[PDB]
């Protein structure tokens, strides 16, 4: 899997592939790894599907209860902290890599990265999963400060396409989401819509 | 396997208004027979029987625990257990130990308390119930006795024909395995009577 | 490594065991008694891993004697066999399995003589004759050869002597002396030790 | 990590008669839980009077069949006479024991008319121990097949039944029936059944369908 | 398997069951475990049947070559040593073989027990096999050097029978062979079922 | 290795090297053996008594084994070689067969050795 | 085992084989691998058979309680969540691969549940040893908004492909159609293979088998 | 190759009237990395034969050079005799079995397809030396996925046209691209026929992905 | 290690990092991985240094003898084939990933990739070593047909720099060689010469 | 494990061995003899792994007797001991190690009685008395207590009987009968088996 988030001014763009695998068999080619933890907080899920689904539902439950009792929209840092506490306390028994991204009025668009082992880092762009390895260079070169929302969407699409073509575990369609004060705009890129890059073609 | 440690064979068959349940008699530790009189078929009712093959210790233990549960059931509810209900009880008992399983492969054979419709079933190590209309088998020699049953069995058999079929199948099957044999006992259950016969078999 | 043998008869059960307790190679004891009287007319013979034998034997002995004191009548041999089998089988699943191989011999006024056999996995079987240990492999054929259900007790001690001198002839370990005793309606009777010098 | 063996399945059976022998086998080849092909006969005509059936690792089966064909040609060239069934069996035992320390994982049955004109069946362990028998079943469903063969052909555990000599038609029906049952309750067996009848006239092939899984 | 052999005044008896097993499955109940190495000495099988058959057949051809070259039949001791030296080359390579080479020579009746481990030993009574432990006791009780030929036949037959009764992996029919100074004779082949009828 | 046919057939079908070696035997010191019912005797002619020789070293009658003995004529060094090879064969035969070597057997071994040299390459 | 499911225009169709294999011998035929969870929710099972049976029964009982209390038909998401949470708690040691299918107020829902607690909502799913062949059939011929007969034909074709190609599967085919209006549980919908006729009768006549002893105990019918 | 390093995924083949067709994705994968994405895993051994490979690509290139030299030697002899598809399949079976017997297996799983003497040959070889002929063949995960479709179609209709076979293999390749992780979009189709072996260039699967708007 | 080569019209550009690591300690921080096999044929060496050096000297021995015998400049296909034969014959014993590149009169610039296990494939561009993973995306995105020598040098430098930044096993200086009909043009980028890309700011 | 014992004296060496051979739990033979007569005035007592004992012993036997045949005199006990040590050590690192534990006893006109000890690792040590096997542990201390370098041969036989009685009492395995042989200037002299 490849999961990728990037922070633009006033929001975030999240992106992920649709492929989940058991060995070399693609059990689901249309999986949705971008889940709503809250109305404006999402998590990109990478690692064991069962572990990630369980932890995502638990954090959704806790953050909803916290949000209602505080009578305030929850904070992305709060969601990331809950994810960290769970993943760290169960680091031995858990195999999950999460990118927590969302928008809150206090701190704007935020992206947080929870790798395996239970640590929290805030990052301007974060990539995770098996396929992020192949696109570290592309994101390092391509990333520029102060990208627009559409520019970040194209950037995420291109990176995920590269990782998808170069990684067997990654594949399918690209699922993209843009979270901001206005709301979540979710889109799926399929077939020709997915960015394509030339082959050597001797 | 641990199941092969003591060794055993149990069979049940369905005729017309009758059932037959048959099992070997050997008790031996990996190769050395100790006794030719082991009880592997136990009565769980007037015309309901259970047959256990596997480890001798778990055979006796699950038989005793099931009789505990069944006697309390019969006293509390004032009726004889239906065969399907005994199947479900045995499955619950075995699945209770899904980890660290009792090493047995039970077989239930009996007639319905009222209809007298015949019932045969088998359960796995961890209580998977399988109900069949022709035959069920369990033990080390499942392969041989499966083939022999698949050939010999015919639907709507008479009691005498059922006895002949089950006897031939058990004898010829236990002849072709090392760890089971030393005689075989056949119980025939009919609505009006129980007939138990011990066959003449190779003591090798 | 330890030998138990039991012969049932019309009105008796004969039991014998080797008298050796041993370390690695040294035979620390020449007169070890592996027979425990649970009651007046029942004996328990036990062999197995060290410690487990004496612990389990003593536990069953004290439970049976508690039954005697509480209820005023002795347990039946069959009931004692089922009880010790239950205790052994429960421990098998547990983290403290008693690795013990037992032979229970008894006389009941109603049901006559009985010999019972159980392995470390806690199977139980009534038998006309039985043996435990590596020597059992050598000596069972002697019993299977010359045994009769109507064997008299003099014939039984003779048969046992044949079985044991076969161990003397062929078995690798040295089991020089054996203890012998009979249970009957009168009760447990000690017999002269069958000693092959 | 690399395992030189895989069990490709298959069942082989052979029966002997006073003036005939039968060698029969399924035609399913399957690795693991997948069928490779539904028409792979396990039976090979070594000569006019003999058939061999092989079951187990198919690579070893092919190699051993080619070896026996070459050795039969060699014997014919050297001695100016075709090999007898017993000679074939002894040679096969020698061949199998040659690789004692890296064995062929194959179960072989030799079925053919003997020199006297009687039917003869020789059954082989993988390591080359060979035994003449009236009938034998080998392969995945050997345990299923052999008890009924022992009862019907051998009249074992039957009293007050006359021991009729086996006939070609009765043996044929028994073969078809036992293979139907083994197709019923063995996963590896069932694609089809090839029956090869060896008699004084020669080999004759009969193919009957069996249950596709 | 259970095999049995002993020497008495009128030669050597050899007895064996006819069961061959693969795990629990009884592959054959009519194997001829006693191997007729040559007209004058014969061997038994225990352990690996293929190993025993192959190596004893090789011994047979070597014995025949020795007979042709030296114009005298090989002694049982010499043949046992040929077998032992042959198997010792492959020590530790997985050979499981148990053999009792039985015959006559200038010495007298000769019985040697050869093993894959390498032991070669002469003795009045030997038994090798899974049921050998059960067979040994009855054989030891019955055996005496001064024994009638019929008495020795009875002892060997019943010994193999009781061993089959106790041991799981030994069964079938009790083949019996008697070695006499002229050569071996196949005295009987009794099924253990009819023997169960007889003895009990 | 030196692979050459020292011995070959000649016209009239005689092996000249073997005949010449027999001539070499003829030159050697006499030996005589007489079989007897409870005894067998061997005698040999001292070629000359140097009056300084140690009698022990020059003996031509040698024991191949306890049960068998030999005497020779011809080249003494070749005799010593065949004697040692026969002795080791005696011991190996005893090892393999657990019986003493018979005279026919050891004679056949020596004969086979000599014949091999008459037909082998470079000997 | 092959179990498979598809969502058609107004409901779900579920399908499974009827073979139970212990090792490589067919322990049973006509086994039922389509289970009852609720009137509107049925579930196929694969993996460890006892685990499938017991977990399906437990969730059936819990949903019976839930539906009784709430007074409205149970939702499919509730079944999915119960199943996945139990399976996740047990960490795959209970071995069950489940195709969960039911219709509810929201609509038709098909879920695929793995032993470790993963779940996936899909239009079509397959599980068991024959999942790959069944998925090949589905990937080839599935189309959206199929009719009920078309969906039944597709599921039958997929389970048949699993039957013939895969060793572990093979017996009659079962189908189950859940719609908003009705349920049709179809024990054998198709019988693709049948046992051949026994040419020779081996029926043993009376007296063929010897008996050492006999004891007839009369039963007091009353 | 005790351990495969760069591997190729399923090869498929189906016999049709007047020839055979085989197809394979142009990919070599290094432990779930699509490292080499333009490689040909199909060989033209002679006019009447094709060979396609799965597994270690290095072993396939070794067998390419060996078998190419063999056919070249036969052409040098020029005696009017040429190796048949059955003959090449037999030699390959021998080579793979021998290397297995020495415990240095060639990791490949092979499909040999040819058309000679008015007859179509389609044969399989595995690293262990298992070999057989069938109307349709598939390797790797193709055995699990594509072979059911091919078997259903062939069982319904034993003999197929070239157009039907090409549509069928393309359909199976789309299924493989959907459900196989180690697969790649680009593939080549090679058909042996009376004219000869003709291998087409890279071809596309033409997927749907309409399921995404569900869920 | 990170090695890469890219073909341009009339020649090749070769590139490599300059770090050899034993465990986590940099044994040589200025090692040269662009070994010469002939005046116009080079090998980029990745994997075990002992194995790569051994096969390189063996191959230059064989290729030099071959070239003097034939009295013509050697072919890069010949060099790659020699490397391939050695690596395949000893695939179990030696682990080595090699990119062979050079110039011939007949074929011009050629690049061949001989990964572990001894397959050989010509490539318009190749990357190898531990660091190649992290720049697959960059080379896939940025590669273009018809790049000049200077453009290829810049591409090689940027890719190797990204890989060196993101990979522990690759670091140091970038060693760059351009092989053409004229001859080798070896150059080294030290310190600030190495291309740099901004780290994420937060 | 089989028992070997040796007790050297002023003009003799006494050697004894158990007479059993065993397969798994059963003594196949009660009269097995573990003493090998390598020449008139040396014995080699051999215990160890099955097959290796007899094979190695017979090799040493043939070589010693070949030495006698070719040279006209017998090897001395020390030379024989060093020879078997050489052959055993040479095979220790080979593909075919002999797991064999030896006790070599002899007499020489010049050097008098000699008893030698070898382990399966082929370390050679002359000893006044020595033993092999698990029973050596039990019996050596008795030898240490009651041995004197000037022991008479009758007293030595009595000491041997003491050690074997201790084996009967304590050693778990059954060693019912023991061979006894003595080597002196006259030659190897067989003695009646000590028995129980």
Image (spheres, coloured by chain):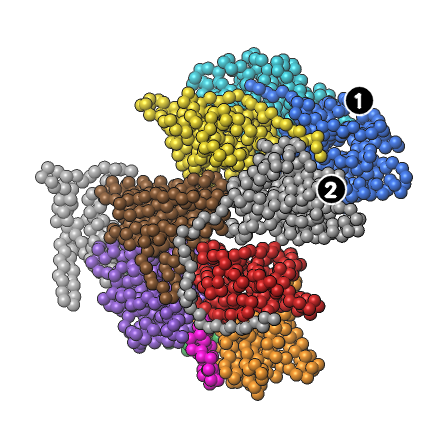
Chain colours: A blue, B red, C orange, D brown, E purple, H yellow, I cyan, J green
Looking at the rendered structure, the number of numbered marks drawn on it comes to 2
Q: Is residue J164 above or below residue D174?
A: below
Task: Name the chief secondary structure element in magenta.
Answer: helix
Closer to the camera in the image, D176 or H191: D176
Q: Secondary structure at mark 2?
A: loop
Residue hosting label 1: A148
What residue occupies the far front of the structure in this picture?
A: G222
Q: Secondary structure at mark 1?
A: loop
Quick check: marks 1 and 2 in contact, CB under 8 Å?
no
Q: Is residue C186 left or right of residue H65?
A: right
Residue C156, magenta (yes or no): yes
In the picture, the disc for residue G104 is 2
Q: Residue at x 23, y 44 (%)?
A: D81
**Which chain letter goes with mark 2?**
G
Image location (x, y in percent) of residue C121: 58, 66
Q: Give the foreground label among 1 and 2.
A: 2
**Which chain letter goes with mark 1?**
A
Quadrant of residue C181 in the image?
bottom right
Task: Measure the C-alpha gap from mark 1 to mark 2.
Answer: 43 Å
Q: Is residue C170 left or right of residue A83?
A: left
What residue occupies the far top of the structure in this picture?
A: I182
Q: Residue at x 49, y 18 (%)?
A: I75
Q: Is residue E179 left or right of residue H131?
A: left
Quadrant of residue B57 in the image?
bottom right
- What span is in magenta? C137-166
Image location (x, y in percent) of residue H108: 49, 34
Q: Residue at x 51, y 20 (%)?
A: I76
Residue I54, magenta (yes or no): no
Q: Residues within 10 Å of mark 1 (few under 14, many from 20)?
A: few
């Amino acid at each position: 899997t490849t999961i990728m988030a990037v922070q633009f001014d006033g929001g975030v763009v999240l992106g992920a592939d649709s492929r989940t695998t058991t060995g070399s068999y693609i059990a689901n080619r249309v999986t949705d790894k971008l889940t709503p933890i809250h109305d404006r907080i999402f998590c990109c899920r990478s690692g064991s599907a069962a572990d990630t689904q369980a932890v995502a539902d638990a954090v959704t439950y806790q953050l909803g209860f916290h949000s209602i009792e505080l009578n305030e929209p929850p904070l992305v840092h709060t969601a990331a902290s809950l994810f960290k506490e769970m993943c760290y306390r169960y680091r031995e028994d858990l195999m999950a890599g999460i990118i927590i991204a969302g928008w809150d009025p206090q701190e704007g668009g935020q992206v947080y990265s929870v790798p395996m082992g239970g640590m929290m880092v805030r990052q301007s762009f974060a990539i995770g999963g098996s396929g992020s390895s192949y696109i570290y260079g592309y994101v390092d070169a391509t990333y520029r400060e102060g990208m627009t929302k559409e520019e970040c969407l194209q950037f995420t699409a291109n990176a995920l396409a590269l990782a998808m073509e170069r990684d067997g575990s990654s594949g399918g369609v690209i699922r993209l989401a843009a979270i901001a004060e206005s709301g979540v705009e979710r889109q799926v890129l399929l077939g020709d819509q997915i960015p394509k890059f030339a082959v050597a073609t001797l | 396997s641990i199941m092969s440690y003591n060794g055993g064979a149990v069979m049940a068959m369905k005729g017309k208004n009758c059932v037959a349940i048959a099992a070997d008699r050997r008790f031996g530790i990996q190769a050395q027979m100790v006794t030719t009189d082991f009880q592997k078929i136990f009565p769980m009712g007037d015309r309901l029987y259970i047959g256990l093959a596997g480890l001798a210790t778990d055979v006796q233990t699950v038989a005793q625990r099931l009789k505990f549960r069944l006697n309390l059931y019969e006293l509390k509810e004032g009726r004889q257990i239906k065969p399907y209900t005994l199947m479900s009880m045995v499955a619950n008992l075995l699945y209770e130990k899904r980890f660290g399983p009792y090493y047995t492969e039970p077989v239930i054979a009996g007639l319905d308390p009222k209809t007298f419709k015949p019932f045969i079933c088998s359960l796995d190590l961890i209580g998977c119930p399988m109900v069949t209309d022709d035959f069920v088998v369990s033990g080390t020699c499942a392969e041989q006795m499966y083939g022999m049953c698949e050939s010999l069995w015919e639907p709507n058999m008479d009691p005498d024909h059922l006895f002949e079929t089950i006897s031939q199948a058990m004898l010829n099957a236990v002849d072709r395995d090392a760890v089971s044999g030393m005689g075989v006992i056949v119980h025939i259950i009919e609505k009006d009577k129980i007939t138990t016969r011990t066959l003449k078999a190779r003591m090798d | 490594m330890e030998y138990l043998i039991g012969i049932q008869g019309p009105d008796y059960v004969l039991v014998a065991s080797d008298r050796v307790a041993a370390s690695n190679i040294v035979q620390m004891k020449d007169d070890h008694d592996k027979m425990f009287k649970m009651s007046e007319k029942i004996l328990l013979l036990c062999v197995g891993e060290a410690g487990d034998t004496v612990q389990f034997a003593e536990y069953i002995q004290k439970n049976v004697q508690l039954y005697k004191m509480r209820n005023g009548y002795e347990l039946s041999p069959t009931a004692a066999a089922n009880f010790t089998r239950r205790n052994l089988a429960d421990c098998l699943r547990s983290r403290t399995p008693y690795h013990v191989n037992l032979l229970l011999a008894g006389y009941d006024e109603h049901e006559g003589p009985a010999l019972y056999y159980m392995d470390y996995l806690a199977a139980l079987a009534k038998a006309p004759f039985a043996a435990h240990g590596y020597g059992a492999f050598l000596t069972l054929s002697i019993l299977d050869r010359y045994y009769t259900p109507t064997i008299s007790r003099e014939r039984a001690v003779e048969l046992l002597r044949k079985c044991l001198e076969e161990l003397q002839k062929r078995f690798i370990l040295n089991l020089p002396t054996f203890s012998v005793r009979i249970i009957d309606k009168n009760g447990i009777h000690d017999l002269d030790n069958i000693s092959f010098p | 990590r690399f395992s030189p063996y895989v069990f490709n399945g298959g069942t082989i059976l052979a029966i002997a008669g006073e003036d005939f022998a039968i060698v029969a086998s399924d035609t399913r080849l399957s690795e693991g839980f997948s069928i490779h092909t539904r028409d792979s006969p396990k039976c090979y005509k070594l000569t006019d009077k003999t058939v061999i059936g092989c079951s187990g690792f198919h690579g070893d089966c092919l190699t051993l069949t080619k070896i026996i064909e070459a050795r039969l040609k060699m014997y014919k060239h050297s001695n100016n006479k075709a090999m007898t069934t017993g000679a074939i069996a002894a040679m096969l035992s020698t061949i199998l024991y040659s690789r004692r320390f890296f064995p062929y994982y194959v179960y072989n049955i030799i079925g053919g008319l003997d020199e006297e004109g009687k039917g003869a069946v020789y059954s082989f362990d993988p390591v080359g121990s060979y035994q003449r028998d009236s009938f034998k079943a080998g392969g995945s469903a050997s345990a299923m097949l052999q008890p009924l063969l022992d009862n019907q052909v051998g009249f074992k555990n039957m009293q007050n039944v006359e021991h009729v000599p086996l006939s070609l038609d009765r043996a044929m029906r028994l073969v078809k029936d036992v293979f139907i049952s083994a197709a019923e309750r063995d996963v590896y067996t069932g694609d089809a059944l090839r029956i090869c009848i060896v008699t004084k006239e020669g080999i004759r092939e009969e193919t009957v369908s069996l249950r596709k899984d | 398997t259970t095999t049995l052999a002993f020497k008495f005044r009128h030669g050597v008896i050899v007895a064996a069951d006819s069961r061959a097993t693969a795990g629990a499955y009884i592959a054959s109940q009519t194997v001829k475990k006693v191997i007729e190495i040559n007209p004058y000495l014969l061997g038994t099988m225990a352990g690996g049947a293929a190993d025993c058959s192959f190596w004893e057949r090789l011994l047979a051809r070597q014995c025949r070559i020795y007979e042709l070259r030296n114009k005298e039949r090989i002694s049982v001791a010499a043949a046992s040593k040929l077998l032992a030296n042959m198997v010792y080359q492959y020590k530790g390579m997985g050979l499981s073989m148990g053999t009792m080479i039985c015959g006559w020579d200038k010495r007298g009746p000769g019985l040697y027990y050869v093993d894959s481990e390498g032991n070669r030993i002469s003795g009045a009574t030997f038994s090798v096999g899974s049921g050998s432990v059960y067979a040994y006791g009855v054989m030891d009780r019955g055996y005496s050097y001064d024994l009638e030929v019929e008495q020795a036949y009875d002892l060997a037959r019943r010994a193999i029978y009781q061993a089959t009764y106790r041991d799981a992996y030994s069964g079938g029919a009790v083949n019996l062979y008697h070695v006499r100074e002229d050569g071996w004779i196949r005295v009987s082949s009794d099924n253990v079922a009819d023997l169960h009828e007889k003895y009990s | 290795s030196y692979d050459r046919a020292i011995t070959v057939f000649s016209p009239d079908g005689h092996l000249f090297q073997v005949e010449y070696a027999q001539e070499a035997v003829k030159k050697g010191s006499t030996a005589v053996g007489v079989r007897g019912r409870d005894i067998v005797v061997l005698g040999v002619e001292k070629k000359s008594v140097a009056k300084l020789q140690d009698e022990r070293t020059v003996r031509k009658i040698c024991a191949l084994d306890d049960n068998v003995c030999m005497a020779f004529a011809g080249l003494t060094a070749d005799a010593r070689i065949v004697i040692n090879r026969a002795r080791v064969e005696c011991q190996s035969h005893r090892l393999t067969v657990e019986d003493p070597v018979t005279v026919e057997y050891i004679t056949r071994y020596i004969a086979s050795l000599k014949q091999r040299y008459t037909q082998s390459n470079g000997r | 085992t092959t179990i498979a499911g598809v969502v058609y225009k107004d409901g779900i169709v579920l399908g499974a084989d009827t073979r139970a294999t212990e090792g490589m011998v067919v322990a049973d035929k006509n086994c039922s691998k389509i289970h009852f969870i609720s009137p509107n929710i049925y579930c196929c099972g694969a993996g460890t058979a006892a685990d499938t049976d017991m977990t399906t029964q437990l969730i059936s009982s819990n949903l019976e309680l839930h539906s009784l209390s709430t007074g409205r038909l149970p939702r499919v998401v509730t079944a999915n969540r119960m199943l996945k949470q139990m399976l996740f708690r047990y960490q795959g040691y209970i071995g069950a691969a489940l195709v969960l299918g039911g219709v509810d107020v929201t609509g038709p829902h098909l879920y695929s549940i793995y032993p470790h607690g993963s779940t996936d909502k899909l239009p079509y799913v397959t599980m068991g040893s024959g999942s790959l062949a069944a998925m090949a059939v589905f990937e080839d011929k599935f189309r959206p908004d199929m009719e009920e007969e078309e969906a039944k034909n597709l599921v039958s074709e997929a389970i048949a492909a699993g039957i013939f190609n895969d060793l572990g599967s093979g017996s009659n085919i079962d189908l189950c159609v859940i719609s908003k209006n009705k349920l049709d549980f179809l024990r054998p919908y198709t019988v693709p293979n049948k046992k051949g006729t026994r040419l020779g009768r081996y029926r043993c006549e009376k007296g063929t088998t010897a008996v050492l002893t006999e004891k007839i105990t009369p039963l007091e019918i009353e | 190759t005790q351990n495969p390093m760069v591997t190729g995924t399923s090869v498929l083949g189906v016999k049709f009237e007047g020839g055979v067709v085989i197809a394979a994705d142009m990919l070599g994968s290094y432990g779930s990395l699509a490292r080499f994405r333009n490689i040909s895993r199909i060989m033209r051994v002679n006019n009447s034969t094709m060979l396609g490979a799965s597994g270690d690509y290095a072993d396939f290139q070794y067998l390419k050079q060996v078998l190419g030299q063999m056919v070249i030697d036969e052409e040098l002899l020029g005696d009017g005799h040429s190796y048949s598809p059955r003959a090449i399949h037999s030699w390959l079976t021998r080579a793979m079995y021998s290397r297995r017997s020495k415990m240095n297996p060639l990791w490949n799983t092979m499909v040999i397809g040819g058309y000679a003497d008015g007859e179509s040959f389609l044969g399989y070889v595995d690293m262990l030396g298992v070999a057989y002929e069938a109307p349709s063949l598939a390797t790797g995960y193709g055995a699990y996925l594509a072979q059911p479709l091919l078997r259903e179609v062939l069982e319904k209709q034993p003999v197929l046209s070239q157009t039907e076979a090409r549509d069928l293999v393309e359909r199976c390749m789309r299924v493989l691209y959907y459900r196989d992780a180690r697969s790649y979009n680009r593939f080549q189709i090679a058909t042996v026929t009376e004219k000869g072996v003709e291998i087409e260039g890279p071809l596309s699967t033409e997927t749907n992905w309409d399921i995404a708007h569900m869920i």
